[PDB]
Image (cartoon, rainbow, N blue to C red):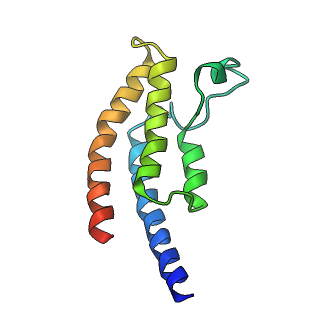
Amino acid sequence: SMEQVAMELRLTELTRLLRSVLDQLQDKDPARIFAQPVSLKEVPDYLDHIKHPMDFATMRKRLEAQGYKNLHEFEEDFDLIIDNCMKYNARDTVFYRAAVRLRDQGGVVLRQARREVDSIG
C-alpha cells in the first residue's frame, strides 16, 4: 500500500536521524571503551553479572537493520551501555568514569534529538 511506503519512509528518516545521534554519542567516547561488546573470552563471568550486554557496534547493527521503531528504544540501548558499566566496574575505575562522562555529555545530544523527533514527527 501507499500507507506502508509512507510508514517505511518515516522509519528511514528516523534511522537517518538516529545514525547522526549515534555518531554524536560515540564521539563522546574517544577512548573507545564502549565501541565493542565486552569480550567473554577476556571476561568469562560477565553474563553472571550483566544480563543484557550492550555496546555501540551492537546498536549500529540494529540501527542499520532499521530495528529502532522510536527514540525510546534507542535510548534504552544507550542507557544499557552506561548502566551495565557502572554496575560491573567500581567507582574508582577508568571504565566507570568513562560511563559517567558519556552519560553527562550524551544528555545534551539526546535532549535535542527528542525535540527533533517530536518536531519532524
State the residue at coordinates (56%, 37%).
54
State the residue at coordinates (30%, 56%).
114
Is residue 61 visible in the rendered structure shown here?
yes
- Residue 106 spot, x, y in % from top left: 33, 41
Left or right side of 36 for 70:
left
- State the quadrant of the C terminus: bottom left
Report the number of discs: 0
Left or right side of 51 for 33:
left
Q: Quadrant of residue 118?
A: bottom left
- Residue 110 spot, x, y in % from top left: 32, 49
- State the quadrant of the N terminus: bottom right
10 vs 26, nearest the viewer? 10
108 vs 66, nearest the viewer? 66
Vertical arrangement, residue 69 with respect to residue 56, above or below: below
Q: Residue furthest bottom?
A: 2
- Residue 41 spot, x, y in % from top left: 73, 23
State the residue at coordinates (61%, 34%).
37
Is residue 95 visible in the rendered structure shown here?
no
Q: Residue furthest right?
A: 41
Vertical arrangement, residue 79 with respect to residue 92, above or below: below
- Residue 112 spot, x, y in % from top left: 26, 54
Vertical arrangement, residue 49 with respect to residue 32, above or below: above
Q: Quadrant of residue 79?
A: top left
State the residue at coordinates (34%, 30%).
101
